[PDB]
Structure formats: structure tokens, C-alpha cells
Amino acid sequence: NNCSIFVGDLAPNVTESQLFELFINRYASTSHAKIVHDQVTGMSKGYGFVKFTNSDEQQLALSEMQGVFLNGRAIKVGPTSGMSQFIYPVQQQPSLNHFTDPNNTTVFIGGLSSLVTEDELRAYFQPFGTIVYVKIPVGKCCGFVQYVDRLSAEAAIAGMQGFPIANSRVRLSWGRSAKQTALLQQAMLSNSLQVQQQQPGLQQPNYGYIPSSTCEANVSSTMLPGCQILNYSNPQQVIMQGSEAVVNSTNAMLNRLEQGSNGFMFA
Amino acid sequence: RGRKERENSSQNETLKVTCLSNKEKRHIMHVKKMNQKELAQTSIDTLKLLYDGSPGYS
Amino acid sequence: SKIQVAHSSRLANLIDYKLRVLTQDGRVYIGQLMAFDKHMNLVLNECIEERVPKTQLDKLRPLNIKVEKRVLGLTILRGEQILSTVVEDKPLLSKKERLVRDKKEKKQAQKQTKLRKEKEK
Amino acid sequence: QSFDIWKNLDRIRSTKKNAGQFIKGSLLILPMRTEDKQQFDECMDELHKYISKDILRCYPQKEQKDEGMLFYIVLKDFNILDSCFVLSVLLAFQKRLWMAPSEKSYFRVPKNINLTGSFYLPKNIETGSSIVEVGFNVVPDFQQFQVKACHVSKFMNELSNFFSQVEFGKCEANVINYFKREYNRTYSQISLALYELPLIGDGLFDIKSYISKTRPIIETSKAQMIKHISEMKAYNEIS
RNA sequence: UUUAUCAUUGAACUAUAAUUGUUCAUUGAAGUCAUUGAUGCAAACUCCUUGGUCACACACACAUACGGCGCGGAAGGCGUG
């Protein structure tokens, strides 16, 4: 619930530790407490906020601290939050499946003919973005393509939909990883919870990375914003983006054409 | 009024009048007055807080 | 304009009439007077200022005349650069209704003086 | 129909329902570019022998690049037929130099060529297909109009259907010099932008402060990326 | 229908001007927006404020031209206490 109480008219010799001792551990459990001090002087202005988890304990603390002796003066611990037309919109949650997760960047591919390999399936989904693994289940005619970016997954689904691989139309949707699929199979065999977990984020902001950018290959980088600074390596580590990237990619694609004209690789 | 307007209007239908008590209309008109004054006093202030880190904000 | 302006009235009696006041230029102001003074400085409610252009003046010299009207609202005009004033349009409420309104204003003013005498005690 | 200009000119004179009246307050500007001048001069002398001086005027450049010239062709107070004739001749000539260097006829258009061009008009237009408008024009005052991939008769019919619907009027007097100054200013800006292309690294970006301004930040971002890779490896691990 | 800045010079120039006129430009002082602008002309549609939206009747009067001989309201003139 996180009920907030606003203590006011406090004394000057009352720090955040004394307010946390007077708020928490007295028939309640205050989650946070912060006294609003001055911006440049450092002295307290006499006001402070205390946010607790339960609303009943915060209401009991506000009813018990109404007029209590706080450093020689009153506490005034009445609540701050909790007929206008304008109210903020409130929403429920979609219970966190693998469709309604905005951080879910792995695409479930199906409808295969049990004939495509892993390197060839990497070669289908390589220029859409950087990639981490292309492993597929055996005998299940399906697979998993996990990117790093979500816009790369959007481009992959918007381009690769309706594309027949080996005379067999593709089915693109969302899905979890292999460990989460094993956890869902273990929780669905007994049918107790069958709860999923959200995919972890990127610990944003990230100034250096540019989305939907691939690089296969000393480095004197100027770190200019028009170019690229950092990138994810192709398996995996973090590489500094050099200037001789399009040259190495051109040499790599010419080598790929030379080795694919003969039959040394099918991808 | 005209005759044929009276034979047309008194035969179509009879509508229902809604009406409220004294405290209900008083509370509703007081809420409408506070809404009219809070709309007359408000203004959109999105461009001030949306360009807050702009180099010409100062 | 069949208004029949009063035959023995002055500026104290012509108050709240929709005047059509003429100036030295001819910039005619139309509006209700609400006050005057010794120099004939006239405030004008819902006033409009009308002129004629220089091209329309040739047609006006011996029919339709396209006057230029600007809206001033509540203005206060000086008595130096004015020439003549007439009464164009009658007000909304009548003489008996203004008499009842003036009696209500007198009774309200006497009640306000009784309230000031009660607050002074 | 045919590949001749004059037969389509007779056809467009015939069945356009008294199209002899010109447009009041009409203006068109066609800026074109030629590799050489001597081949252009004979065709322009033939055009001035065919089209009068009051209708069409020509404006040279200042010879700043010395290789690519820029010539303005301003059609002022023109009729609908002379506009089609001038645009057909110029759109044939500025592509015949690349396609047919051995045909040698300034008024006979072959069949292998398609007419595709771009011409400016003033903003005060009222239209109330092969010729389209543009979005995000580069000129502040004028509107760019595009024609693409047409034969001779389709070019005639489309230009006549375009000028039969549009309504011009009230152009500014020395708007030609205004367009000249604005066009030269815009393309001098993009030429200066191409001049800024070798000056990216260490030239004019204050690299000495920009390295120290972003030296801890890229390191912390790289640490966040390494933490993201390690957390992804822990997330995909069965164990 | 009518206007949308001047001056010095360069390559020609009509030329009594502070090269006025014609094509191109460097520079110098202010530099209304408006050209879908301004003036004149002309029609149609729509919407706002006002009323006695009143009492009887859907009626054969008048050269002294019109029975002003109902209940009022709005503006005004004249006369009396």
C-alpha cells in the first residue's frame, strides 16, 4: 500500500535517524523515512515523509503520534496522501505471460520441416540484430531465437512472417527460454502455480549502444555520437566499435560468397 | 399554435421529466461551480516541464 | 429613426442612451454613455467606431456606403476632439423599470448605511 | 501516339477545348544542369527562335564550381501549349546527353527514353496521375512537382491535365532573384556540409574535453553491458 | 484593377540627377506582417438580440377619403391641479 505520513513543525536537532527511530519499531514497520532539508544550507525545514508498507499501521502511528513530544515540540504526523474531475488513470496487470512482457525479446519459431540446421537458422536471423544462441529442440520442429534488442525482434517478426523455410511456411510468436520452459513443464505436471518470471532488463540508461546494429569482427575511438561506441560481440563479450567494421564485414561476406559457391557451408 | 401541429404533437409520444430533491441539486450545482472555477483557473503546463533540460530553458 | 428623442432633456437625462457621437474627423462612436463631466468626457459601453474610406467618399459626394467599423468595447473618450452628439437607440429597460431599479438602489443604499451604523456601534 | 513533338502539339491544340488562353499571374521555374555549354546553346537558340523573349527567360550561374553549370529557365505568363513544348524539349535534351549522343536532333524524341523531371511552382496554387506533389520540400517559398517515366503523349496529356486544374495568381515581382539567392544559399550549405566531412575526427569537435567528459560514462555503460550478459547467462542456464 | 526599396563600382548602355532605364553581382542605413494582401462591385445561404408574437371576428368601407368609440405597454407633444 505504501501509506505516507507527513510530520511537520519538527525541531532543528532532529535528524533522519531520530525520525526513523520514532516512526519504525513502535507497533509498526516504516519502510522509508526522509526529512526534507534545505537545498544548499543543509538544515531541516521541519518537515518529513514516512512511507510504510501497511496502511493500518501507518494510520495507528498517525493516531498515536498526533500531539506526541518530538524533540521538545509537537509531532503533527497526520497523513499526506489517502471533488475534482481530473484523476490519474489506474490499470491492472496482464499477470505477466510471455506475450505482454515488453522486455521479452526471444521469438518462438515453429512450422519447420525438421530439416534446417542451427547455423542456417542463425543465417536467417543474423542481420536483424545481434544474437546469443540459435539452439532448437530435436524432433519438435520448432526453435528459439533470442536477440538482445526488442526492436530487433519486432523487425524479425515483421519481416520473417509468411516466409517459407524449406517448402514449409513459418509460424512466428513469442515464448520463454529453455529453462523457463522446463520450469513451466515442471509446474504444469503437478498444476500448482505455473507462474512465469519476467526477463531482466538492460540497466538503462545506456548512451553508447545503438539498437539494431551488428558487428562481426588497437582501437582509437573518438566516441562520437554519430558513429557507434559499444556493441555486443557475435558468439560473447562487449566490443568497442572500431572504424574498420564495414571493411571487415565486406571481406567476411566476400569470403562467405566464395565458400558458399563451392559448398563448404550451407548458411 | 396551429391545429395540425396540435394533432401531430399530442399523438407522437409523451416524454418523461426527470427532477431531483433540494440537497441533491444543491450538491450537484456546487460541484459544477467548483468544476467551472477549476477549469477557468487551470492551464496546460506541459511545455514548461517538458523542455526543462533544454539549453535555452534559462 | 422614429426614436423621438426627448424635447427638453440634457446630459443628466440622456444617460444610458445609445448615443451616436460625432467628432472633428467624423470618426463616429456608437455606444451607451454612463458618465460625463464639465469638459464632456464621455465613457462609452459596447462602443463601435465607424469611418468612411477615401474611396467611398467619391461615391458619397453627390445608394450604399460601406463604412469601416472597429469595436472598442468600453472606452473613455475625451471632449476636446468631439464635435456633436445625438441619440441613436433607446436602451433595453424602460423609464418605469429604471424608476423601480432606482428605488431598489436607494433602499439598498439606506440598508447599507444602517449596516454601517450597526457596525460602528 | 507518335514520337514527334509537333504532332502531339497539334493534338493538344485540337481537343483541349479552347486552350489558347494563358493563365493570369502564371510563373514556372525549371533549374537544370548541363555538363557542357556548346551543345546547350544551339538548342536554346532554337528555343528562343520558337518561343518569344517575353514568355521565357534564362538565367546563368556565377561559375563557382567550374564543372557543373546551373541554368534557370523561367516561364512567365505562359500558355498551356508553350509550357508543354518547353518542358518536352528540355526534358528530352537533359537526358539525350546521357542516352543518345549519336541521334543529333533537338526536336525528335526517341522511344527508348522516358521523361522524368522536377519543376518548381509558386505556393499560391489551387487545384480545385503522373505529376505528383512533394512532401518536405527544401525551398521555403516554392512547391516542387514531380513527373516520372512517361512517353511523349502521356507527358502532353498529363501536363495539360495538370495546368487545366491548377489556378495561379498574384506572383511577386523579383521573386526570381529571391529564388536564386535561396537556392544558392541552400546548396552552399550542403556543399559546406560536404566540406565538413573530412573534419570529423580531431578537427572541430573539441575532442580534448569530449574524451574526459565521456571517459567514466562509457566505462560504466560497458560494466552494465557485462552485467547484462552475465545476468542473461544466469537466466538461460538450466543448472 | 493596382503596388511589393535607394545608392557606389565592375562588362555594354539609353544619357540634362545623387548612371535615373535595361541583365548580372560586392558593399552600405533603416528595412510592418500582409499579395490566400488592399480597393471597388454584386448575389445567395446560415446564425445571433428585440417585441402584446394580445381580446372578438375571417367580416363590404370610402371626397368633409376612410365610424382613430377595446385592454394595455414603449417614446414624445400640449393642457390642468
Image (tube, coloured by chain):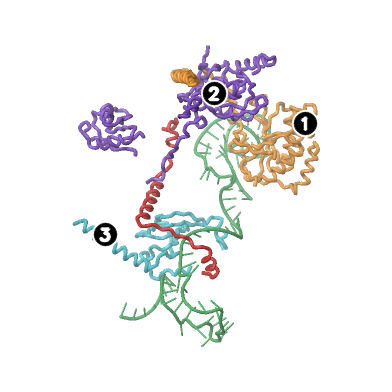
Chain colours: A purple, B red, C cyan, D orange, E green
Per the image, the residue denoted by label 3 is C112
User: Looking at the picture, how far across and down is residue D220, in whole percent?
Assistant: 44, 19
Q: Residues within 10 Å of mark 2 (few under 14, many from 20)?
A: many
Q: CA distance from mark 2 to mark 1?
A: 49 Å
Q: Which corner quadrant of the image does residue A110 belong to?
A: top right
Q: Position of residue A25 (x, y in %)?
A: 27, 29
Name the residue type under label 2. Tyr
Residue at 79% x, 43% y: name it: D11
Foreground: C30 or D230? D230
Q: Quadrant of residue A50?
A: top left
Residue matched to label 2: A147
Mark in the foreground, 2 or 1 = 2
User: What's the amino acid at mark 1?
Assistant: Asn
Q: Do the residues at pointers 3 and 2 share their chain?
A: no
Q: Nearer the viewer, residue A235 or C9?
A: A235
Residue A194 is left or right of residue C76, and the answer is right
| Left-right relation of C117 to A135 | left
Q: Secondary structure at mark 3?
A: helix
Q: Could you tell me if residue D210 is visible in this image?
A: no
A7 is higher (above) or lower (below) than A130: below
Q: Are marks 1 and 3 in contact (CB under 8 Å)?
A: no
Q: Chain of mark 2?
A: A
Please, which residue is most extreme toward the left here? C121
Residue that numbered label 1 is attached to = D112
**Image quarter of residue A259:** top right
Residue D69 versus residue C51 in the image, above or below: above
Q: Residues within 10 Å of mark 1 (few under 14, many from 20)?
A: few
